Length: 34
Length: 165
Image (tube, rainbow over all chains, first blue to last red; front, top):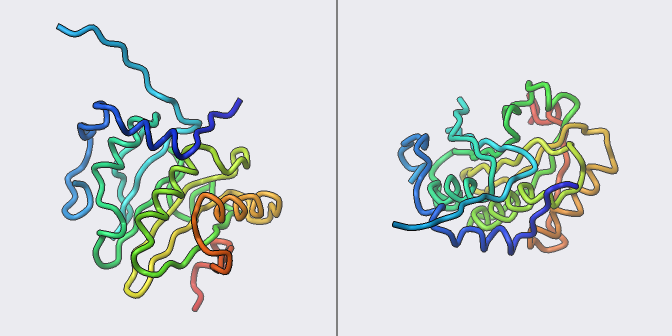
């Protein structure tokens, strides 16, 4: 019962406003974390 | 005054992004959506500078050979000409997160390393001597990655990678 996702599905999951904000915990590293 | 529902697609494991120029954690996520939040707010490895590495390992597994999960472990390695690292890294981790490798618990994580004249992408597994696992990992890499068949893939134990030419 392994959770399996094909590439196309994962790509389409990016099309959600949930993804449009950074994680609060995101460290500010110059040149790495935008 | 909205009326909303929210549910996210779980992953088989929690994963942690790491960075190195000392390896430091960027963050940990447990859902496809949370992954894109971290990924979309990181520079792509192609647009990276100097001698830096990204790591994406199962939560709890540090991206170091010393970690108990990486005892008796090894990795497949792909050396890439400049310009391929961003696309390959994306395809690799999407394949890892999507459980495309189908080797049970054997996967530890993935690395991409930008160097001077080339880039290197690798995926680590727990048991270097498990030939059935290392071959299945090999076969999945050639698929999910879009590399020519003559692209050389190297499998090395972690000890093979330490203190050697």
